[PDB]
Amino acid sequence: FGTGFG
Amino acid sequence: FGTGFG
Amino acid sequence: FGTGFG
Amino acid sequence: FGTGFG
Amino acid sequence: FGTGFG
Amino acid sequence: FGTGFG
Amino acid sequence: FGTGFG
Amino acid sequence: FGTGFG
Amino acid sequence: FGTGFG
Amino acid sequence: FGTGFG
Amino acid sequence: FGTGFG
Amino acid sequence: FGTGFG
Amino acid sequence: FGTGFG
Amino acid sequence: FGTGFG
Amino acid sequence: FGTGFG
Amino acid sequence: FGTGFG
Amino acid sequence: FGTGFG
Amino acid sequence: FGTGFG
Amino acid sequence: FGTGFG
Amino acid sequence: FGTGFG
């Protein structure tokens, strides 16, 4: 899995 | 923004 | 699956 | 906006 | 399936 | 707007 | 199936 | 939007 | 197989 | 957005 | 196999 | 964003 | 195998 | 921003 | 960000 | 796994 | 094997 | 910022 | 940052 | 084997 926010 | 996969 | 918002 | 698939 | 709004 | 399929 | 509004 | 299968 | 977009 | 499988 | 983007 | 597998 | 980005 | 995978 | 395996 | 913020 | 970055 | 892997 | 193994 | 940096 992979995730990011910004 | 935010994103994810898995 | 995959998801995003922004 | 928002989106998803799975 | 797939979905989006915006 | 909004959309989906499945 | 598929659907949309806007 | 659109979808199909076979 | 199947595909969709929106 | 879009998705597919086979 | 499968793929998607958004 | 995007993802796939096979 | 699989891959994703965001 | 923040990100992770695993 | 991104990730993959095989 | 891997993670970062900033 | 696997790899990722962010 | 901060980061880690393992 | 990044990481990998095999 | 494995490697990483940050």
Image: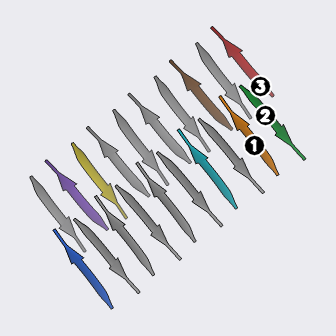
Chain colours: E brown, G red, H green, I orange, K cyan, N yellow, P purple, T blue
Residue drawn at x 21%, y 42% is: N1
Q: In the displayed structure, does residue E4 sit left or right of residue I5?
A: left
Q: Are marks 1 and 3 in contact (CB under 8 Å)?
A: no
| Residue T4 position by quadrant | bottom left
- Point out which mark residue H3 bears: 2
Amino acid type of the residue that numbered disc 1 sits on in the rendered structure = Thr
Secondary structure type for disc 3: strand
- Point out which mark residue I3 bears: 1
**Residue N6 x/y as whole percent:** 37, 64
Is K4 located above or below residue P1 in the figure?
Answer: above
Q: Are marks 2 and 1 in contact (CB under 8 Å)?
A: yes
Closer to the camera in the image, T5 or E1: T5
Q: Nearer the viewer, mark 1 or mark 3?
A: 1
The chain identifier of the residue carrying mark 3 reads G
Residue bearing the label numbered 3: G2
**Residue N2 x/y as whole percent:** 23, 47
Outermost residue on the top side: it is G6
The answer to whether marks 1 and 3 sit on the same chain is no
Amino acid type of the residue that numbered disc 2 sits on in the rendered structure = Thr
The chain identifier of the residue carrying mark 2 reads H
Q: Marks 1 and 3, how far apart in space?
A: 12 Å
Q: Nearer the viewer, mark 2 or mark 3?
A: 2
Is N4 located above or below residue E2 in the figure?
Answer: below
**Residue I4 x/y as whole percent:** 72, 37
Q: Quadrant of the N terminus of chain K?
A: bottom right
Q: In the displayed structure, does residue G2 sit left or right of residue P4?
A: right
Residue drawn at x 81%, y 28% is: G1
Q: Are marks 2 and 3 in contact (CB under 8 Å)?
A: yes
Secondary structure type for disc 1: strand
The chain identifier of the residue carrying mark 1 reads I
